[PDB]
Image (cartoon, rainbow, N blue to C red; front, side):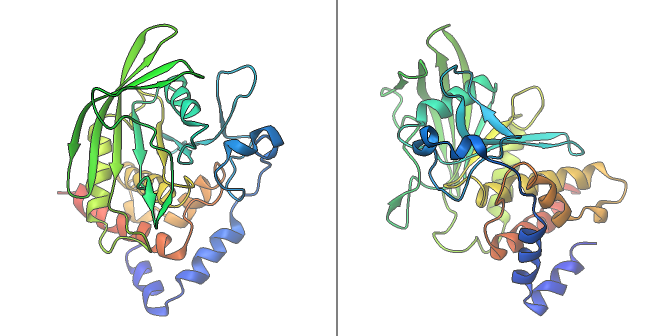
Length: 282
């Protein structure tokens, strides 16, 4: 069981100790490509790089690099692309990746501005009539519709490969209310967000992996995937309580470093899964 296991840590306060064991056990893989100098402006944080083994490659010949990782959860049969909030110079790459990976959903867990600084570029159009052209990657992005809700917004976008004139509907699931500090108090809205992404079919294998990012693409991003996978595994397994969220996180950290940036985020993932497991079964 993992809910009793929750109190066990809450009462001992030892979330730090747990989370640090995760950091200590977490896999360590080369990120050669990320650290190459030409890609230095393709990274938002020096300390957040995709492993070479799991990194998304852009179908460019020059520089296939984007700071994005395929998290492939075999047991849960879920894939996610975790990426950083795009940079001014990588917005085109981000959409190229979306396109090339046949993603349906983009999940954004941060605001463009947080704590008075730009956490990522404004990489989607904010008004229907002001489409975005990404000339480097020959993509056109159009806001089609936007459903703004209390804790998150869902945007229908139209991504058009200008080279081939195919267009796809991309959903942009934008969680707008993660607090500037720490983590939400209840996971209720994060789960509604997750279930919203789920209900869209953006997590389903008929599509490319969902693209999820926050600023680094590991903190809140990790929390999103970890909760989704954990919940999906609880539905899939004969014994739901057997789902060990540390074990899941560690599996996910084989694909991208840093997933879950703090013990408070770890705690919240527990909360999210614990509370999420409840909701599924009614």
